[PDB]
Length: 96
Image 1: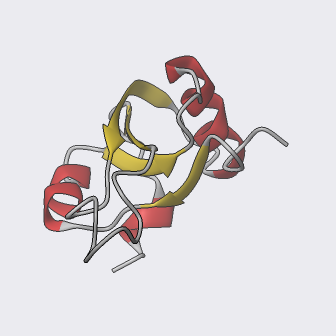
Image 2: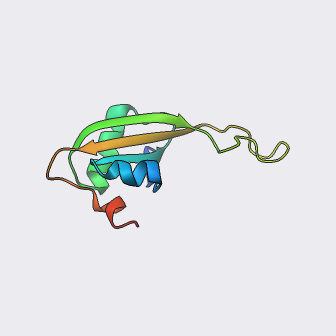
């Protein structure tokens, strides 16, 4: 199932995200490969919503290092999915 699997795994709840969801945009944690359009299908299968715009960017651990060698900027990607008007993914809306 190439849905929320490899592509968009779990949602990210944060000020820049919660106050962002405000418009319907949803940032997600996803593998460094889920083609932009692929992310559209990942949430469309689980969130069963309508993706009207998906913007993803590479995300690295906060200090991308944590003390001495103990992680180092890994390879993580974030995905912001927006849905048309009238829609609203409840996966992050009730995740507060």
